[PDB]
Amino acid sequence: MIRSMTAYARREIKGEWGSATWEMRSVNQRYLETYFRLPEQFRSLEPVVRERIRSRLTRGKVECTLRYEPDVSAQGELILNEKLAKQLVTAANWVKMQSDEGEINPVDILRWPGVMAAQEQDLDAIAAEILAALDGTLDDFIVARETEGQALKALIEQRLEGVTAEVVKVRSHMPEILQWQRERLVAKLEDAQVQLENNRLEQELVLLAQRIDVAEELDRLEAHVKETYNILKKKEAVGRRLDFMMQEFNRESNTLASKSINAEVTNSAIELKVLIEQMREQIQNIE
Amino acid sequence: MIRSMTAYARREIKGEWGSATWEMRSVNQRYLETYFRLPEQFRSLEPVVRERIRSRLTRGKVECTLRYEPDVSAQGELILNEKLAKQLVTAANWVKMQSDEGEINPVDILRWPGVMAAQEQDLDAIAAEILAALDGTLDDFIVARETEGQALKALIEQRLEGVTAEVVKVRSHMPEILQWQRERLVAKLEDAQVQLENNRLEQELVLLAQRIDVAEELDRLEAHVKETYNILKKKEAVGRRLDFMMQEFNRESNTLASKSINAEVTNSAIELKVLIEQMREQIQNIE
Amino acid sequence: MIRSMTAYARREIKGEWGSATWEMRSVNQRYLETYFRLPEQFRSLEPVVRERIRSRLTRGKVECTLRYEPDVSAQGELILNEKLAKQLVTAANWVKMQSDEGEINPVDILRWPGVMAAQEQDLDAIAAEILAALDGTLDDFIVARETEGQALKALIEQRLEGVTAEVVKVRSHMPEILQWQRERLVAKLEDAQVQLENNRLEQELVLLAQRIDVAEELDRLEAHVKETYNILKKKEAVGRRLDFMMQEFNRESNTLASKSINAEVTNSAIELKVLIEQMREQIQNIE
Amino acid sequence: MIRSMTAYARREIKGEWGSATWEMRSVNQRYLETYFRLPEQFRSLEPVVRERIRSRLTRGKVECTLRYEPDVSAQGELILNEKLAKQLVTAANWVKMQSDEGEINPVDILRWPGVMAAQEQDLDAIAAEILAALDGTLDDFIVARETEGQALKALIEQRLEGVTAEVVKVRSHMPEILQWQRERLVAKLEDAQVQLENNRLEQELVLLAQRIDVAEELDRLEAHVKETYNILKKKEAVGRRLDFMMQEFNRESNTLASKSINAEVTNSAIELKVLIEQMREQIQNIE
Amino acid sequence: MIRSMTAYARREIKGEWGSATWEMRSVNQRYLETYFRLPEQFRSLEPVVRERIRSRLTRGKVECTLRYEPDVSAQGELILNEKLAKQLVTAANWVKMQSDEGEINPVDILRWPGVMAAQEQDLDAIAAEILAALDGTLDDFIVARETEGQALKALIEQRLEGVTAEVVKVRSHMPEILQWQRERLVAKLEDALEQELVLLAQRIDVAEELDRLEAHVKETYNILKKKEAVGRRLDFMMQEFNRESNTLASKSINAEVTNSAIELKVLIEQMREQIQNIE
Amino acid sequence: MIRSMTAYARREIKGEWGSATWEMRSVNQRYLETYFRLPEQFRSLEPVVRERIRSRLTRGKVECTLRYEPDVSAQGELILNEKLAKQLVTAANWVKMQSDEGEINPVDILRWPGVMAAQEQDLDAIAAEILAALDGTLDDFIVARETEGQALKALIEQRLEGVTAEVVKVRSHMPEILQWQRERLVAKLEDAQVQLENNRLEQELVLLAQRIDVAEELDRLEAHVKETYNILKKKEAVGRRLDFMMQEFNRESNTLASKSINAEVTNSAIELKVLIEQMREQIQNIE
RNA sequence: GGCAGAAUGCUGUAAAACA
């Protein structure tokens, strides 16, 4: 199915251990790039979440952020290190003896690293819930991508309908275009004949006759819109395939615009460029 | 109707507690880029804000910054962890017995992590007003775009009037230059004392007239100014269509300059090219 | 007069509130692009500053940066969160009751986050001074543009005198076209020893004399240097008009080089192309 | 054998001293960059660890973390630095003389870095096992890379088979396209009432056919897929070479698309570009 | 002499204040375009630096970056903001009212941000030394252009020697060409007219083409020693070379002269390709 | 005399006070950054050490470790910045005048950054010997860098011999390729075409010869290996100069691949890019 | 108009680069 490369997904899980929030953002990119902002406590989950991301997403820069705020009140009571505190007090008394003046601060002893440390919580139980929330976030992310992808497909199918209409309007002027093609070649034949001892006369006519195929340019445009409809229903990653198709649309419209056949044909040729330009806008953020 | 691609809208809301400001900027771009700088608390508004913006704007580098200024005075009172504070004080008194000296600092106990924190935020109600301000800011942003859009349209229309005047001037000058060549050619024959063959002079003068015939270029230029006037009345965005029309304008001006032989016609062609360049400069800012 | 596109202006203002610095720098550009890097407190000045910049300037890549350095101490007494400071005192007092001993350091409460809110500034009287500094910086920027522009005008006029000198040299080293081809044909036909008709041969000499005659090309070169002098004295924007004029200068030099039949003319054509190239380089710096 | 730049490997050793864990993770990178998260006890092993990894590996970003968990008995209690403590007391007394007031806080002396530091064991025997454990991790790392690289090689081979199929399809379609295009071009001249020498016209038709013939491009594509198979069969460092081969693939496909006439050839060129893009995506993750 | 538009030059000036590294990098360009990445402290030097560079270079896209690494110890001695300290003391006194206890610590006031900030550096004598390094870097930059332009000059002179050899080879066949031109003139006359004959005589003969080629070679040799900006002048000379050789390429008499003309065209194309990257 | 950014130098100094070991290690970096592991006894030597190291080095991440083993016979003292220590006390006294209370903690003055600093003028007997040991260690570190960079120079020059081999290899294929194109073209015209019509065969071959003419790229490649040899003997910091040279190497190598019409040349141009990639990897280690 | 392709604009590349 058609998918977009700009989606936002968010999930949050709460419990006695605390609250953990998963956030996922996507921006357009040629390849798949994953950047993580995991907390230091759960730094060990990076390979697993990276594999989970790469297993479902196929293109676009992805930013994943995990915020973990433990419940301090629900945490176990802090335990006082009896031996470590006693060691510091005896050591601090020695410094008082050398300096002959001192005042032990009881809070400063408690603030020392190690002493008065809370018991470590069971991170293994939290990891499973966090991974479940990550899977839910991936599901929401894919749903958001698909929801916006349908909008892009509708916009592109709207533009492609206009391209066929513009081809029909240009085909309405074929009797005038065919008359113009003859005059382009007839004038060149006699213009070169007026010039004397001019070589490569046949080369000019042969090259010129190849570059006035207005009928063939419309056929290729009509063949691309038929194919572009088929590309949109491939159910695979067609983001890049459409990007290479837009270059073929650009190639045909560029040659048609430079013809300058007629005032009314020029308006349609300008419109073809506009439709392709608008169509190329949507292809940028398709996956 | 038409809109400028650069604008600036700022809206500030003074709620019961705190205040928020919505700021929008826009710069010229070939596609639509929407960059958001939302605060940490309201980071989840991006999908809602992005949808509400991409549905009203077509092109430009739109940057939206939401600045949240909480009222600490009106903020919820910090909750004091009585049990955690009591645990530290009793443990501090344990050190005091062994140290035999020292006084517990009341501020130091409060400075301990987890003793005091903001228990409640209640951001669901305050986020509704912020989103409501966004709809107001977009309306001002669109009006700012349309206000500057009219100046661009007026400038483009003035330059189009100048283009029509220059075309009329060239058309007026053309017959005199056509007659000037005939007098100069016969003068050289008279100066060379050579009697040209019958119908050779008439045949030769046809080639020069074809060389200096710019009627088709002027007709195409008038058709292009009429088409540009029609385009400027369209409700859809016309930045790309006008930018493509300027290419046809440039083609006609280049052909006129190339086929020019008189100083006055060359000066008029240069004036046409200057007018087209000014038109394109104004077009770059059109939606 | 004419103004260079690249310039640099800087202006610093001091006061009891602090220091502010305006820096404006521009470089060559096809159109007018203005990028503003304003401080956070003064982001609301962007529309006014942009309007003034666009009013004063025609084209360039102008970038304006405002550096704001508020004084740390201002507005008399420091702004204190009275509720938060009082709230911590009550909480600290409760800790004293349990421990029966303690003291509250005033700086400890001041160092508490939120108690010392960001110092309030008027931000309205300072805006007038900043806008006045912006106007002064615009005056300096325009003066610097005009000073550099006068040097560019001298360089262009020096090369224009070179073009007139080269045209004089060509008109003196150019032999009589009718006589030059007559002598060349006679010698070549002397080997053939057969002449179809002397009467018809003389007619073709005059008709095809203009093919190799460069008198017409030289007159247009002399007409353009007179026009280029006139363009340099206009009050409007001149860079675009002169840039399109150099195309006409190059058009004549190419035709003069191709039509050249003598080494002196060809060497002069190269010299003309060098002078035009040197003259075209300076025009790229004129707005 | 071909290897990948993304792999994982973990090794742990259990002993009476404690438990040490080695973790290696690789992410694709242009060059080799090594980051080490080593404990303070084994910080001196970084130059030894870095040399072993840089010698065995060639490319990719590698992050190696050594998780050292000593036993309670193996932990060394903090030892007071009496020599350093007495120096600070003398240093503090010098400042007291300048101020004539103040008292030295005994805890503040202890909190000074280096005064209260745990004794460091020899750990020479323990580190000897760590290096052997690290060498085991590196041995499994290469094996881990090789298994992952086999899938990439299989994918690249499948896409190369698709490329060969597309090339043979284009070669099958081409002669009919060439035959019809020549027939259409000569018929176009007849409709324009242009009479040309058959010998001269036929010579121009042959040269134009050589201009629009794509046999050489397909031959180059076949040679490129054969060389790609050889490169895959090569031994080491076939990432960047293979990427350059993909650049050549893209060049040939772009030439084929630009020189194409029929819609089928254009569709085949689009398919070739899609296959080359997928190969580039896979190859970006190859050492 | 000949200057190549691509070069690199680096100079580092070191001192008690820190370091300052100038890194000029240049590639090809039709005109002179300079881009600067200056540190925030020395961004005001752009007009002075830009003027200095524009006066010593003629073409190329120059990218000059100044890297400033100020020293921590180079900062001035601390000064006391008496206005800010007094405000903090009054602010501290307010808290003492509610608490009705406590003593303000003088050092804690000094530890507050902004009350003992160091004096700003002069940044005036430093800029004088930085501009001295820029002047030196340009001298190194020019040498890097000249040491690369000598190779291009040698290649162009080699191609010019090849062109002279080809011209001599063509001149060795002058009587054969002269006979061919007479037959061509008679053939058109005997076909029957005057319209075609007059322009045929107007066309440049082969000997004049070779003389113009030799004159172009001599002028190119002089230009390579002109000792100024000769990139565009050499490009125009190559255009003239192409215009002269097109006649020989078009004319067909025999295999040897055709091969010599093809060699001349290839040599002129190589010269033109190598000219594009000379300042 | 190329210096590499990876080196190691250890120097031990023995005296009556004990044994002091200076170790210096360097790792690749874009700029110069120094980290010190001085014991707190000699912590005040950090500014002088940093000044000397930044004076004698240009680029690279440098880690310096000093191990000090004092003896009971000799006792040292902490070097203090007397000028700054007295200034802080004077400033504190001024604050005491306004507050009319307070006391100065001696440890607070010492903890102030810059107070625990040393200068070369005021150094102990041991400190001067430590500084001399550091000078010797830095000289040995420079020697190690020079002798490690000699290996890098050999590695790079080995690749440069490959580049000249590829350049002379392509130069032999070029006369064969152009000659082979002649046979292929006349084979097509050998069917029923008399190629002796004007010079279409020769003009096409001339046009083809100018399209595939890679002589300009090969000469610039050869002129860049001559200059790269001289850069490797400049006896200065040429790490960045070589990096810019490789960009010029890749610029000509990639253009050679593009203009190539034969598979052998393209396979050679791929080899040129690989040699550049191998050289680029070593250049990252060059100071 | 960094180098180069096709014919203002679009691709390849330096760019897994430089801010």
Image: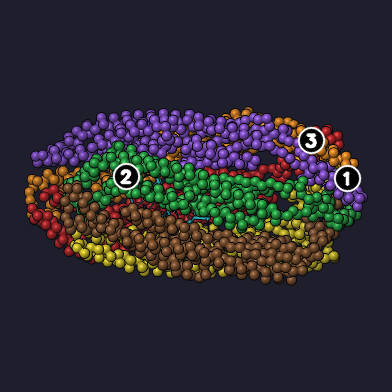
Chain colours: A green, B purple, C orange, D brown, E red, F yellow, G cyan
Q: Picture coordinates of residue F273 (x, y %)? A: 46, 63
Who is closer to the viewer here, D184 or B203?
A: D184
Residue C235 in picture, x, y percent from top left: 41, 31
F150 left or right of F199?
Answer: right
Residue type indicated by callout 2: Leu
For the N terminus of chain B, the image quarter is top left
Mark 1 — residue? Answer: B103
Cα separation, mark 1 vs mark 3, equals 22 Å
* Rendered residue at 10%/39% (across/down): B199
| Neighbours of disc 1 within 10 Å: few (<14), some (14-19), many (20+) | some
Q: Amino acid at mark 1?
A: Glu
Q: Which residue is mark 2?
A: A256
Q: What numbered label is drawn on residue C87?
A: 3
Residue C24 position in % (x across, y down): 53, 38
For the residue pair G13 and F84, the one nearer the viewer reads as: G13
The image quadrant of residue F179 is bottom left
Q: Is residue E66 visible?
A: no
Q: Secondary structure at mark 2?
A: helix
**Chain under numbered label 1:** B
C93 relative to A75 in the view: left or right:
right
